[PDB]
Structures are given as structure tokens and as C-alpha cells.
Image (cartoon, rainbow over all chains, first blue to last red; front, side, top):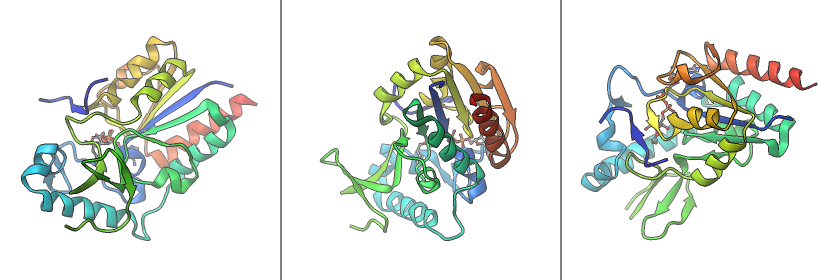
Length: 9
Length: 224
Ligand SMILES: *C(/C=C/C)O[C@@H]1[C@H](O)[C@@H](COP(=O)(O)OP(=O)(O)OC[C@H]2O[C@@H](n3cnc4c(N)ncnc43)[C@H](O)[C@@H]2O)O[C@@H]1O
């Protein structure tokens, strides 16, 4: 789960 | 009949005239995601962000924008499977609904809805947003919608199909792994191999308008 997040930080 | 869970992303609506995120950059409609796709972007320049989504909302409702063959095939799939079918989309468009699907889970929200930010209530909205209301759209750093029902369906699925999604954005990109953990057969249908394509047991590449009806037809005929 977790928040919507992109593979690069 | 098998329990089928379908995940869709922007690629299934590309051929319908809704342009996709160009991977070459970090830009959406010539905008940086940080500026139009984060809560922070909204706080710093609310009127630009409201204008950006006002534009997306209008473009969505233009006559030349319609469901394509891929959207239609998923409506036929739901017709055949009933409550053993669940469609989850990352898209904010309404093309699944216009194609005939029902109970579509919009885990990243909907362009045709806005949200009164004090409340949690989403409200139907088809026009511009003027002068605080915000788009009912899940931004980076925010929790996707409907996750409880999605993860339940992932644990129950006999077949998990991911369509038109690049595997960059979590948690959606992790659904294939979760499905595999609970024994589902996994299928990737996409223009090109995704970032997580290696996780899928079965895969077909090409434009969604061709690949999805082909796969759906093969699935439906294997039933009978
Ligand atoms: C947050 C906020 C939105 C307002 O979410 C959006 C989006 O929902 C999320 C996930 O992105 P995704 O839906 O996976 O889309 P892309 O990362 O842009 O990848 C597109 C995907 O589609 C394929 N594709 C393009 N064209 C086609 C056709 N004709 N047929 C099939 N597939 C196609 C590309 O090859 C990519 O794999 O991130 C955002 O923040």
C-alpha cells in the first residue's frame, strides 16, 4: 500500500 | 467462472485522444508533475493548478474523445462475468463508464468530480472551478482511493490483468506482485513492456485497441 508514489525520488 | 481483476492506466485511453505522460521527461501536458500533481503544488499556486485541471476536464468532454475498442471489450467482459469481475483504474477519465462498465474503482480519483477540502465529500462537477474546492484527484503523497476493496479483490482473483500502465507508480505497480502471492494468473497488456513486466506470467504488446479485444475474446471463448 502506501501513498501514491513514483519509482524515482 | 474465474474471478478477474483488471487494472488500467493511461495507455488504454491514449487511442481515445487522451495523451499520455511522456516518459522522456517528467512532464504532463508540458507541466512538471511537482507543480500540478502534488498537494504542495496546489498550495503554492492554486489558480494555475485549478486552471490545469479545468483544462483537462474540458478536453475530456470534447466530441472527438470517445471510448475505443479496448474500453468496449472490458464492458463486454464485465457483462459476461458479473460480480466475479472488478475493474480498477488509475485513470481520471470516464471512458470506462461511457463504454458501459459499472462499479469502476477510480483509485486515483475522477476528473468529473471535485472535493470540498474541509469535508471528505466528493461532488459531481463537469464545468470549470472558479473562486476552497479542489479536483477529486489523488496527488503524489496522498492515499489512493478504494484500497481496501482492491486488496481484497487481489487476494481473491484467479486472473489479474494490467492494461496500459507503465509500472512506475505505486502502489498500483505493486498489484501484480500481490496478485501472484495469492495465486492469481497474471497478464500484462501494453504498448510496450512495463517497468514491472517481468513479474507477469503472460504478456502481449501492441496498441490497446487491438491487443485488449483480442485477449478478451480469447478469454470469453475459453469459458464456453
Ligand atoms: C496521479 C494523478 C492523476 C491526475 O496518477 C497519474 C496516473 O494515474 C499514474 C499512473 O500512470 P499510468 O496510468 O500507468 O500511465 P503512464 O505512467 O503514463 O504509462 C502509460 C502506459 O501506457 C502505454 N501506452 C501508451 N499508448 C498506448 C496504447 N495505444 N495502447 C496501450 N498502451 C499504451 C505506455 O507504453 C505506458 O506503459 O501516474 C500519474 O501520476
